[PDB]
Image (cartoon, coloured by chain):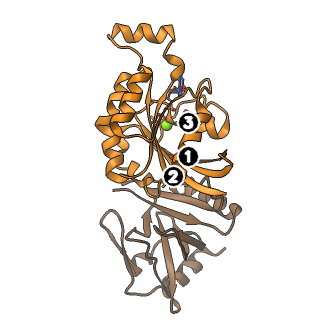
Amino acid sequence: AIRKKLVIVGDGACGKTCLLIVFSKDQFPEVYVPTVFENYVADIEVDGKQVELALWDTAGQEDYDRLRPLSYPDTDVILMCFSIDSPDSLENIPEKWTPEVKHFCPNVPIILVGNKKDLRNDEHTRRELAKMKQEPVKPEEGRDMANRIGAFGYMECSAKTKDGVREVFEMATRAALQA
Amino acid sequence: YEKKVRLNEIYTKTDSKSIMRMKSGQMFAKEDLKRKKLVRDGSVFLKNAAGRLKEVQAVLLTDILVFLQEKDQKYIFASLDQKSTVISLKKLIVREVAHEEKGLFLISMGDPEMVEVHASSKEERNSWIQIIQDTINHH
Ligand SMILES: Nc1nc2c(ncn2[C@@H]2O[C@H](COP(=O)(O)OP(=O)(O)OP(O)(O)=S)[C@@H](O)[C@H]2O)c(=O)[nH]1
Ligand SMILES: [Mg+2]
């Protein structure tokens, strides 16, 4: 009955849409369609507070850079994501997403979210990354990045397994209720 | 529903000095309504940046969507915070407002602009999304 608006941003393919749908529909979306513009809604109760959360889904592809700012007005909390199986997605956090969000939305609380947590200890994933001299993002690296960009909090989740999904939105709601 | 008779009525009733810059750079005016083709018209509400609503007539043409405010017995092109209220159907996408069953989003994808429109009911909101979408798609 309290209304709040959440906007999710982050690199192409890092799991933003699957995270929203898993949360609001409790179903993992099977077919990947890259996002241009969508929006969803879910109710959540937190700390005895009942909140209707508007979920504004945005395009990770830079081809839609012009379009993303239409989603930022009136935002109460931002989920800024990277994928734990993609150290390059983490490095776009200070190089692209934070400067964009600080330009349009400078005083809006950010939850830094590492997605795809299921892949951290997945052997296939580690094996492929190692061929590239890469490793899955470690939780300390995510926490360090959260401090560097001044995020409200830091969470990790897997939409695929549902691990951590409820806690991400609990925290985002607490942040949305702040100020 | 007599579409051409309705369009003539809307033309005759809009104010000859009313104009609206489209996001392309093209200026739309009364005379530009003259030889358009009407798909549907009806009363709807636009949502301001401040969050408040204003009643308008939505006039969907085969190629454009137009919002008109009534002013002293005549139509004028609706004002909405510097946003263009004459909208090309090319590169336009339409979506439900998930948190408001009476609402729809129009996002013009030329810089782009988004406009939030509320029908008087969910059925009307659905009905409007349909016909806007059919017309975009030429069906
Ligand atoms: N293993 C695993 N895969 C996931 C997880 N979440 C999403 N994916 C997969 O990653 C791919 C992209 O996910 P998606 O949520 O659509 O990304 P997006 O960030 O929304 O992408 P875009 O719209 O900006 S291009 C899909 O193949 C999807 O199933 C996860 O938690 N674990
Ligand atoms: Mg997506």
Query: Looking at the picture, which amino acid does disc 3 mark?
Result: Val
Residue drawn at x 62%, y 27% as measured from the top left: A162
Image x and y of residue B28, in percent? 37, 74
- Residue type, mark 1 in image: Arg
For marks 1 and 3 on the same chain, the one whose residue lies earlier in the sequence? 3
* Shade of chain A as shown in the rendered figure: orange
* Coordinates of residue A66 in the picture (x, y in percent): 34, 49
Q: Are marks 3 and 2 on the same chain?
A: yes
Cα separation between marks 3 and 2: 16 Å
Q: Please provide percent x and percent y for residue B55.
A: 56, 77
**Left or right: where A27 falls relative to B111:** right
Whether pointer 2 and pointer 1 mark residues with C-beta atoms closer than 8 Å, the reply is: yes
The relative height of residue A140 versus residue A112 in the rendered view (above or below) is: above
Which residue in the protein does label 2 denote? A178
Q: Where does label 3 land, which residue?
A: A168
Q: Secondary structure at mark 3?
A: helix
- Secondary structure under tag 1 reads helix
Q: Residue at x 41, y 33 (%)?
A: A12
The answer to whether residue B25 is left or right of residue B127 is: left
Q: Which one is earlier in the sequence, the residue at label 3 or at label 2?
A: 3
Q: Which residue is mark 1?
A: A174
Shade representing chain B? brown
In the rendered image, the vertical position of residue B4 relative to residue A25, given as above or below? below
Task: Please name the amino acid that badge 2 sits on.
Answer: Gln
Q: Is B36 displayed left or right of A26 in the figure?
A: left
